[PDB]
């Protein structure tokens, strides 16, 4: 509580109301030097909770206190999260991330006792009950976005033990987030910030969230994939006859094909992270290589532009180029 | 003048005065002086309250402060709290034992009245009462490592519990012993120096053969204190291959064999006990062990129970092969 | 005689164990069970000392087939560890060539590739 209160209320309010009005910072050089120091100070304390997060899972009182902050977070008007508030959010994501519950390391019983998200059935329910509410954040896309990442966690835990009571509430939770075009909020607001290009662990956590989606709930995904492919064709073909398309259309599969296209588009780390999309089998690899082939079925003109952008993202890294060069070669040996 | 009034009065309700002093200090950004004053107070039933108050006030003094001296003083207060707690539980015990021992009460008053040194405590509270658990805790904290001493202490604890449990029904004795052992082990689980596995297991199995208890008791207890199944199996196999004539003398070598069998069967029924990445090799090891056991069973003169055990082992082997 | 045999086993005098076991086989003239037990003990001690040929002879003399087979498995395993594969090759198989093949096959399909030499 103190950590968050001091950091935010001190840095924003003072500089904006005292250092920007009185211009106590003398030259055009001091005003930047002090602003950079404050902006490095905040970014440092956010890296601290970020560095701690990727090592140590959070206890009960802290996870509730980090959730008690992300209930107020805002986004700059210029459509790009300030490098600070963004990393603080991707920090709690790695804390809540049950991607450590999905790794086959046999400390899984020790880590379930150290991760406070578990051992408290009151924890999973309290987060789900709060994100299912209709009081949206200072950015309604926030209540929907966080509601999704938790739901990807409520679905994955189903494998562990027999916690399969909240697996039902992962179907309407993913539909609510998709209906909020969360594939659009993560393409414009998160990756749009040029500071996301810096932190590698901002990429690994999202790449984990994007890869855990089609294989943790390969049932909820295949349903949400098949539903939109059919909802797109029916209306597009009926609009071609005589009318105009409904304004209530939500092409989140297009926005998702953009999101996979914008995320892997830039290559500064030489990771060739697109190696996950190329299969030369673990149940995860089959559910991914299927997702590459199961998505190729759609032929509607509405998803042609994004699926071409998705392949633009997937074709990063030399190996990922040749393979994707061979995929296009055979698809016409007709696929569009 | 509030500060010097407080100091003067505290030097000349001293507890109250020094408490107020430390409070004012912390408010006026002087928690270090608060601490110093509080420690001076601590040093200077009523004494029991003084100790409780001392502990509370030093906890307030160093919330995060890692000041070597003060931090060590707080650790010593926690160890003084250790003293208090162990003293009181064991005093309840020996009081109720010696017709409400008056000497126990006297000793407790002495222990609360002043902080004692290791040597004195050890000697004194050993001859009249033998507080083995407490002695073990003391040595653990200091860092003194004497394997023989540790083993002797463990043995004595068990024996005292057994003397007190003779009155109770076999089942009750067993359960109480189990609980006590588990709790004490959880305290020294990380330290193998203060937990002599081989000796303990051997002595406990001997006690089981003497009191005619269940074969699987030891195995279950060890699985409960998170002792890895591979490790437990290793220990059992080692004990078996040592060819201790004690078992032959007690007319129960087959009992030890059956206990090993029960451990193995429990593993097979719930394979999750062993970590997933070690399962295959562990299965191969079990298959080898089974082979050798079968060979020895076949070098012995046949008996109906022996044949039944042989058949059981072969079935276990088949199941393990199917698993691997 | 069996009591003295158990004595000599803990006593760790293998040769005495063997001769006394032979004398005890003689006393158990009609008892196939006892004969099999003592012969099994003899085989075991010979295998432990490195007396491969004697071990094999004791193995081929055990009346009980199951005991004989388990002893065969043990012999195979031990010779592999000591790298005495030449003698293993020399020793004929009582319609259990395929049995040996299968034992090693199962060992392979159950052990890590980078550690054991069963496959080889």
Image (cartoon, rainbow, N blue to C red):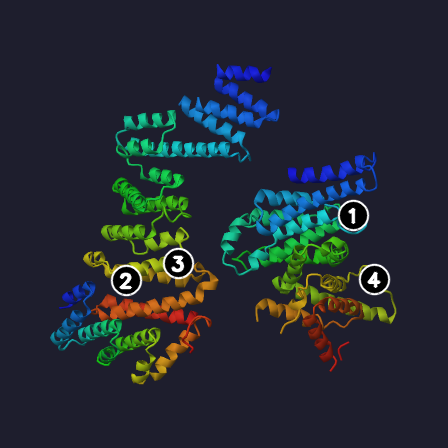
Sequence-wise first label, 4 or 1: 1
Are there few (<14), some (14-19), or many (20+) residues within 10 Å of tag 4? few
Q: CA distance from mark 3 to mark 2?
A: 18 Å
Q: Assign the N terminus of chain A to one quadrant of the image.
A: top right
Q: Chain of mark 2?
A: B
Give the residue number, with chain letter if any, for mark 4.
A246
- Report which quarter residue B118 is drawn in: top left
Residues beneath discs 3 and 1 located on the same chain = no
Give the residue number, with chain letter if any, for mark 3.
B229
Quick one: SS at disc 3?
A: helix
Quick one: SS at disc 4?
A: loop
Q: Chain of mark 4?
A: A
Whether residue A277 is visible to the viewer of this picture, yes or no, is yes
Residues A305 and C107: in front is C107
* Front: mark 3 or 2: 2
Give the residue number, with chain letter if any, for mark 1.
A76
Q: Disc number at residue B241?
A: 2
Q: Residue at x 77, y 69 (%)?
A: A308
């Amino acid at each position: 509580n103190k950590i968050l209160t001091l950091i935010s209320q001190i840095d924003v309010n003072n500089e904006f109301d005292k250092l920007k009005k009185e211009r106590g910072l003398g030259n055009k050089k001091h005003r930047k030097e002090v602003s950079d120091l404050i902006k490095e100070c905040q970014q440092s304390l956010a890296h601290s909770l970020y560095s701690w997060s990727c090592q140590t899972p959070l206890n009960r009182e802290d996870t509730l206190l980090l959730i008690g902050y992300l209930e107020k977070v805002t986004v700059e008007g210029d459509g790009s999260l300030d490098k600070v508030n963004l990393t603080l959010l991707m920090s709690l994501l790695y804390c809540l991330d049950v991607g450590f519950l999905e790794q086959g390391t046999d400390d899984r019983e020790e880590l379930m006792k150290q991760a406070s998200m578990f051992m408290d059935r009151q924890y999973i329910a309290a987060i789900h009950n709060r994100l299912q509410n209709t009081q949206p954040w200072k950015s309604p896309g926030m209540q929907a976005t966080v509601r999704l990442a938790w739901a990807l966690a409520l679905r994955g835990i189903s494998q562990f033990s027999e916690v399969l009571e909240f697996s039902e509430a992962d179907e309407p939770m993913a539909e609510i987030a998709i209906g909020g075009n969360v594939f659009l909020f993560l393409t414009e607001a998160v990756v749009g910030s040029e500071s996301f290009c810096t932190d590698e662990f901002f990429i690994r956590r999202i790449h984990k969230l994007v890869t855990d989606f089609p294989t943790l709930m390969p049932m909820k995904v295949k349903q949400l994939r098949n539903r939109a492919e059919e909802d797109a064709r029916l209306i597009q073909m009926s609009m071609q006859m005589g009318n105009e398309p409904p304004a209530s259309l939500r092409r989140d599969l297009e926005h998702l094909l953009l999101l996979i296209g914008e995320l892997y588009r830039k290559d500064p780390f030489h990771l060739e992270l697109a190696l996950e999309y190329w299969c030369p089998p673990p149940q995860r690899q089959v559910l991914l290589s299927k997702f590459v082939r199961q998505m190729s079925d759609l032929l509607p003109a509405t998803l042609y532009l994004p699926y071409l952008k998705m392949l633009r993202g997937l074709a990063s890294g030399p190996q990922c180029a040749h393979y994707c060069f061979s995929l296009l070669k055979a698809n016409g040996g007709g696929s569009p | 003048f509030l500060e010097p009034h407080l100091v003067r009065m505290a030097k000349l309700n001293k507890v109250r005065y020094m408490d107020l002093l430390w409070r004012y200090y912390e408010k006026n950004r002087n928690f270090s002086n608060a601490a110093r004053v509080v420690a001076k107070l601590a040093d200077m039933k009523q004494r029991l309250e003084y100790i409780s108050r001392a502990i509370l006030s030093a906890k307030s003094s160093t919330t995060m402060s890692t000041l070597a001296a003060d931090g060590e003083f707080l650790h010593e207060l926690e160890e003084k709290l250790e003293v208090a707690r162990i003293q009181l539980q064991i005093q309840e015990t020996l009081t109720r034992q010696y017709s409400h021992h008056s000497t126990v009460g006297d000793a407790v008053s002495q222990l609360d009245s002043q902080l004692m040194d290791i040597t004195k405590m050890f000697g004194q509270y050993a001859d009249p009462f033998r507080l083995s658990e407490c002695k073990l805790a003391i040595i653990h904290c200091a860092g003194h490592s004497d394997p023989i001493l540790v083993q002797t202490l463990w043995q004595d604890i068990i024996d005292k519990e057994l003397s007190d449990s003779m009155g109770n029904s076999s089942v009750d004795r067993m359960q109480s012993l189990h609980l006590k052992i588990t709790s004490l082990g959880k305290i020294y689980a990380s330290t193998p120096r203060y937990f002599p596995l081989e000796f303990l297991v051997k002595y406990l199995e001997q006690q089981v053969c003497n009191f005619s208890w269940d074969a699987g008791f030891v195995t279950y207890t060890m699985q409960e204190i998170n002792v890895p199944v591979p490790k437990l199996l290793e220990v059992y196999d080692h004990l078996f291959k040592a060819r201790d004539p004690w078992w032959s003398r007690m007319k129960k070598p087959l009992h030890l064999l059956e206990s090993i069998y029960i451990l193995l069967s429990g593993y097979v029924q719930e394979p999750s006990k062993v970590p997933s990445y070690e399962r295959r090799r562990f299965t191969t090891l079990c298959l080898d062990a089974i082979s050798c056991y079968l060979v020895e069973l076949q070098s012995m003169d046949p008996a109906p129970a022996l044949l039944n055990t042989v058949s059981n082992f072969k079935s276990l082997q088949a199941k393990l092969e199917r698993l691997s | 005689y069996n009591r003295v045999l158990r004595l000599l086993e803990d006593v760790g005098l293998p040769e005495l164990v063997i001769q006394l076991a032979t004398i005890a086989i003689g006393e158990a003239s009609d008892d196939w069970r006892s004969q099999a037990a003592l012969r099994t003990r003899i085989f075991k001690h010979h295998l432990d000392m490195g007396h491969n040929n004697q071990a094999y002879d004791a193995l081929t003399q055990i009346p009980d087939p199951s005991r004989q087979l388990d002893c065969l498995r043990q012999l195979v395993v031990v010779l592999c560890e000591r790298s005495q594969l030449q003698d293993l090759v020399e020793f004929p198989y009582v319609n259990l060539h395929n049995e040996v093949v299968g034992i090693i096959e199962s060992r392979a399909r159950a052990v890590d590739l980078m550690t054991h030499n069963y496959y080889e």
